[PDB]
Amino acid sequence: DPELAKLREDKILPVLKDLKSPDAKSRTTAAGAIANIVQDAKCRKLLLREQVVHIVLTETLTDNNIDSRAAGWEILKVLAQEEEADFCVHLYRLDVLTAIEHAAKAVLETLTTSEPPFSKLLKAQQRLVWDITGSLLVLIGLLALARDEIHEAVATKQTILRLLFRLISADIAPQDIYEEAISCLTTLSEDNLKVGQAITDDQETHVYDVLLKLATGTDPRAVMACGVLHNVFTSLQWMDHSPGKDGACDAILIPTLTRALEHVVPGGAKFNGDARYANITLLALVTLASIGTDFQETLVKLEDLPTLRELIQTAVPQLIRLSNLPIDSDESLTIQSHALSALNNISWTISCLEFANGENANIHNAWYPTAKKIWRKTILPILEADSADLKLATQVTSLAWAVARVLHGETPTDGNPHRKFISLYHSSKQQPFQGLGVKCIGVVGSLAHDPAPIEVNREVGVFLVTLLRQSNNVPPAEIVEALNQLFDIYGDEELACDKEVFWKDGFLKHLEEFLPKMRTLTKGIDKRTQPELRTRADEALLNLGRFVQYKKKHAP
């Protein structure tokens, strides 16, 4: 390729010689140059071919001049932001974490020294320190997110943690730096024991107390603090069933998060006069969604369940309200999506509990009427409105499935929701257990249980059986869910749908006939690559055999 040779000749080779040499404008200038050169795919790749990282790690970063070190860190930053995660793995294998640790060491020295105190430095100098800090914070987050192994290595770098704690507790860095430090620590504290411990055991800066005061009060950064504290509560297992210092758990954060949601209204979401308050709103929703997942452990292990209690009484009403706001922008659509996400997580967690035989009766009773309200106030209104967005259809269907799993035959029939989900099912196929197809099958089967009307049961039953008869374009995960739905609905000879549908419409012939196709398809699922699906398919194949013999034994 001759166009690459010239491109290499006229923008790559020159700037690299600039990156080199004794001085030193050229280095921040190199960097700034690369910040835009790096943006082009073809220019970025030539630079990597020209060994820029090796240069930066051996020369630019180890330079006595801070203007040079700053330029070096900027270059690694923009590269990491543009490449895939494997680039971060590469920096990691080159031992970039030791260099980051050394730079954070120097930053921390400069911020805490009285010789001279940081405030007494010339503004141009303080800015370079912020330049570098900014680059480091971004890099640390990207690296942690690239691989679990790198995340754990970062957690062992006590000096990185101390820099974060100091930036957060001293509360004297510029706004963007404080926010990036909060965001970085949020990333590092997610599912990480060592980080959680470092935060709660920090008696140099008492970062945990600083965070706790902020999360609980009226500072506009309350929600940011909440994000970090929730991550550590889950990591350390500070929960309802085993509270942390002074009873600490997710429940103590829910008020602040719910408070953030009442400020959202149809009309004003983000302003220039009010910038990125829009910022609190989505962070609150993201945190609420994470709590909705994480609190599963308390349910397994409502005076003793304050988090569940706060989710039902305080959070969910606002989530419902936000889920159904008039859309008048992209912000309102993003907000609706984030609200559905949190509702979904909360609702799925509760529906995974065993309720038959009067188990978890207290939770069931506390939730049931909220389940019905979500069905009526969120699900139905979205369903009416033939939105073509599959993302939104996927979310509403996922939530509906979660809710219908609790309601079953008591799910409202208002508006014939089953027909819309079946219709959604077919339309999706015209544009593994997380597929939209599976979700449609799940919700529709759930609402068909006795005491659903017989014709609701019949339309759903006939849909499910027709998947078995015409399974050419039906993936295994959908077959497995369809079979399981059928087992749940027609397993009882004393229910009206047994004689009035199962036997009358000849479902048995079609189930029995499916068996060979089921054997074939179950074997086709690779155990190495899809062990969870294969396991569920084998169980369904076994139950299909059992169900067929049972129905024959009880044939009318």
Image (spheres, rainbow, N blue to C red):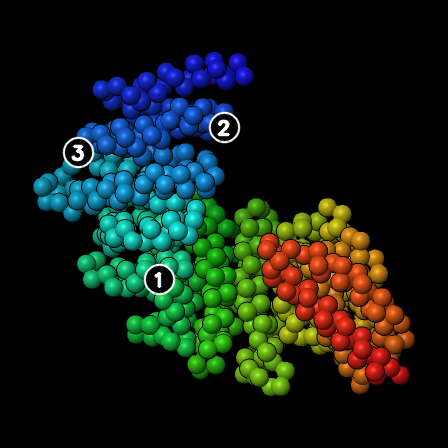
Q: Earlier in the sequence, mark 2 or mark 1?
A: 2
Q: Residue at left 84%, top 83%?
A: 554
Q: In this view, does 508 lie above or below 135?
A: below
Dot 2 corresponds to which residue? 41
Indicate whether 316 appears above or below 322. Answer: below
Instruction: Give how far across and how far down residue 265 sits, in percent.
Output: 53, 56
The answer to which of 400 and 72 lies nearer the viewer is: 72
Earlier in the chain: of badge 3 and badge 2, it is 2
Assess disc 3: are there few (<14), some (14-19) or many (≥20) residues with their C-alpha within 10 Å of its C-alpha.
few
Tell me which corner region of the image, top left, top right, bottom left or bottom right, holds residue 468: bottom right
Dot 1 or dot 3: first in sequence order is 3
Distance between mark 2 and mark 1 Cα atoms: 38 Å
Residue at left 37%, top 16%?
14
Asked if residue 324 shows in the view, the reply is: no
The N terminus sits in image quarter: top right
Q: For the view shown, which residue lies furthest in the left direction?
A: 115
Report if residue 35 is visible in the image.
yes
Q: Mark 3 points at which residue?
A: 122
Name the kind of residue labelled 2 in the image. Answer: Ala
Relative to 369, is 547 on the left or the right? right
Q: What element carries label 1?
A: helix
- The residue carrying mark 1 is 193
Which quadrant would the C terminus be assigned to in this image? bottom right
Query: Of discs 3 and 2, which sits in the foreground?
Result: 2
User: What residue lies at 63% left-to-right and 51% top-to-bottom?
Assistant: 391
In the image, 507 versus 248, the foreground residue is 507
